[PDB]
Length: 50
Length: 49
Length: 49
Image (tube, rainbow over all chains, first blue to last red; front, side):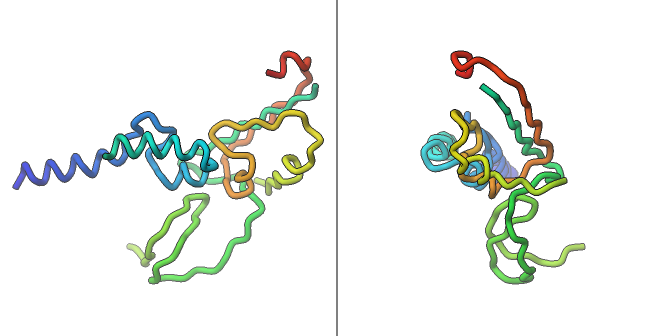
């Protein structure tokens, strides 16, 4: 049970990582940037999260 | 050449300078797109203790 | 502690350079900062870059 809970908790915590992007919050990037560079930031986040 | 550099601070602090938007009403307990002090999001809202 | 109407500046076309970093020029009317440091001076053109 502890191993499964630790794996799930680590997976959740990984969403707060930047992975090189300006912000770990996808909505913040969408609100701050126009698509031409928001897409680069989202690509970094997508790579990290995948 | 006259130059103005406008540095904007986005921190987890109250927004003392905001845009020319229009605050709307409150819809509680219903799935809604929300914008609280610049924090944009999508979700449902409840009264909290 | 003020309302920031940015369309007056970006749609005036009276400026030669209007580059932004971390924030698109068509979305500052939709953003909101806590501290805006307006930096005003004069500089040569070849040094504007």
